[PDB]
Image (tube, coloured by chain):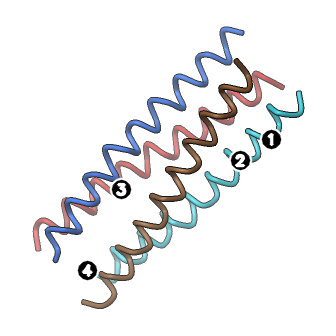
Chain colours: A blue, B red, C brown, D cyan
Amino acid sequence: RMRQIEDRLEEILSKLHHICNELARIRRLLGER
Amino acid sequence: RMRQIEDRLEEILSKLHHICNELARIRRLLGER
Amino acid sequence: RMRQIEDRLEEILSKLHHICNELARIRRLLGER
Amino acid sequence: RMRQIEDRLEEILSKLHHICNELARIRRLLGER
């Protein structure tokens, strides 16, 4: 159903935002070496 | 080369955030259907 | 700590590939509509 | 339209696959330092 698809995209969005945060954190750690 | 890897991660971050924004837009359009 | 950053990037890669797979699945479901 | 959405997801998929390739490449470069 379309609602299942919309929820999955929201779940994907939450995780992608977490991934961005983690990549930004890794970028910061590399810069403080 | 570490500063270059840092720049590449920033370019990836940039594109990932744009992708989040496009997926958010898709999620929104689907909701209007 | 570099080996740990490498492990984290692998964990991110893992999740990003899973996300690609879920988005591919969504693309497919939308096509069947 | 749904076709516009499906095309955009395909375009997003192509880019995400490129991002995965680039993150894997960065992981490899860090491991050869």
Q: Are marks 2 and 1 in contact (CB under 8 Å)?
A: yes
To which residue does mark 1 refer? D28
Please tell me if label 2 and label 4 are on a single chain: yes
Identify the residue position indicated by label 4 in the image.
D1
Q: Earlier in the sequence, mark 1 or mark 4?
A: 4
Task: Classify C23 as above or below D32.
Answer: below
Type of residue at label 1?
Arg
Which is more toward the observer, B10 or A33? A33
The amino acid type, in three-letter code, at marker 4 is Arg
* Tag 2 and tag 3, C-beta contact below 8 Å: no
Mark in front: 1 vs 3: 1
Q: Residues within 10 Å of mark 4 (few under 14, many from 20)?
A: few
Q: Quadrant of residue C31?
A: bottom left
Q: Mark 2 and 4 residues: CB-CB less than 8 Å, in contact?
A: no
Q: Are marks 3 and 4 on the same chain?
A: no
**Residue with the mark numbered 3:** B22
